[PDB]
Amino acid sequence: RSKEISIEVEDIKDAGDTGKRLLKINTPSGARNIIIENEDAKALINGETTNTNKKNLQDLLFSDGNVKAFLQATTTDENKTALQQLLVSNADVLGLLSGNPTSDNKINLRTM
Amino acid sequence: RSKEISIEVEDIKDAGDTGKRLLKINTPSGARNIIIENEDAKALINGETTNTNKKN
Image 1 (cartoon, helix red, strand yellow):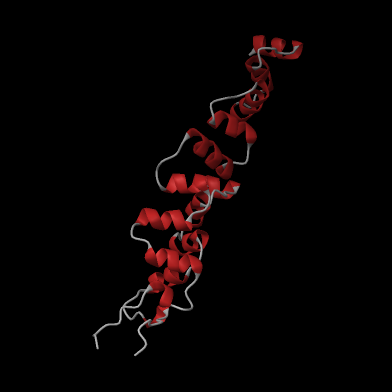
Image 2 (cartoon, chains in turn green, brown; image 1 turned 45 degrees about the vertical axis):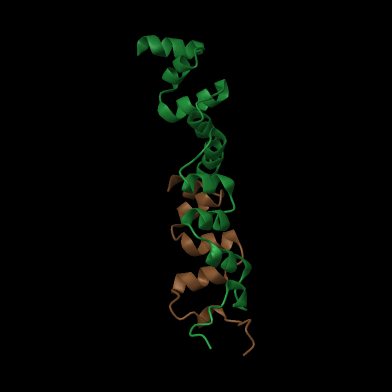
C-alpha cells in the first residue's frame, strides 16, 4: 500500500492562488513573473530594460520634472532655466546662462 | 483507501517558512511581497516609486 502518497499542489486545500502558482514554478525567473506585476519594475529586477522601461522607472524614482528631463537627455528651454537655477546661485550669471541677460545683468556681468 | 489524497500546505513536513508562504499565495503581487524585503527594490519591481524610493 505504497510508502509516500505524494500529494499534488491542488490537494493543499488552504493554499492561495498565487501560492499554488509559486509552488509549481521551477525557476527564479518564473517566480518573478508571478510576483512582480509592474512591468517596469520586473524589467529592472530581470536586469533587462528598454528605453521605455527606463523612462517609466525614472518616473517612479524622481519627483522633479526638470531633473527628469535632464535624466532623459531631452530638455526644453524652460527645463534648462530650472536646471541652471539648481546649478548656479548668482542672479547675473543666471542671466548670462539664459543667453538673454537683462540690462542690470549686463552691467553686473561686466563688473564681475 | 480512496486514492485522491488531499494534503494541505502544513502537511509538507520539510517545507520552509517562506516556502509555505509562497505555496499559499495566490497572485504575483503576493509573491513579490514575500520575496522582496527591501522596500525600495520592491517599489521598483512593482513599477510604483515615490520620490523617497527613487532617491534610495
